[PDB]
Length: 223
Ligand SMILES: [Ca+2]
Image 1 (cartoon, rainbow, N blue to C red):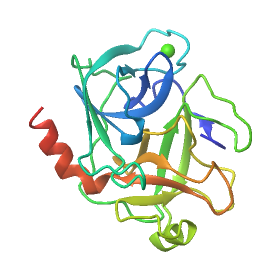
Image 2: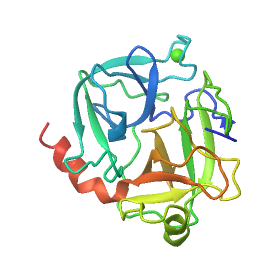
Image 3: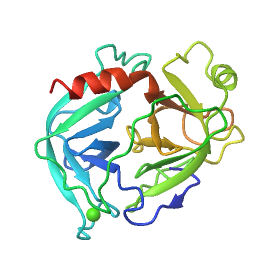
Image 4: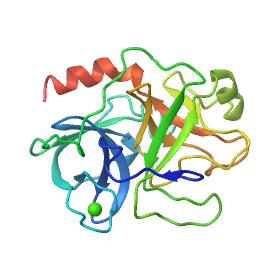
């Protein structure tokens, strides 16, 4: 997260870190056994880390649970990043508490202009590299479909939306990938892609979760 703020320990209790020997992507806990992340975050040997603030210090509220299964969207296209969504099932149920909690799925898609909360342990610089230890947050508005399509001509599908600030300075970034965009209490986006980070006229692009609630529910009902 570029241009963001320190969230405060455990104030984003649905935020997970995916670890394969190191933090490599975010995710969102949607019930005690399931995490939503980005398909482009697929790797084998994932450990889900719940209840994290400082990802490099054991602070006492963590739950580390291995993935039992990963399910990339059937229509995920890594070339275009269309359908950039994946489910991760945990080997054991998380213990839900004040610091580890699920986030609601959407029933309807989010309004343009809605201020949403994006979070993660990704790069905090727009030029150069600095990865934070503690969880960073950013409040960012959903942009109009027209301004999103203008920004990335030919590349935006109905399964994507843009959010952020056209003037630059505030954005999600590498390492935040797979993490949540929460609007009005619902998981409406997943951190997916963008041209650089926090650059003028190049806003963040997010998976539009409300297009996937039927697949999410059917998959969790069968696995
Ligand atoms: Ca920790």
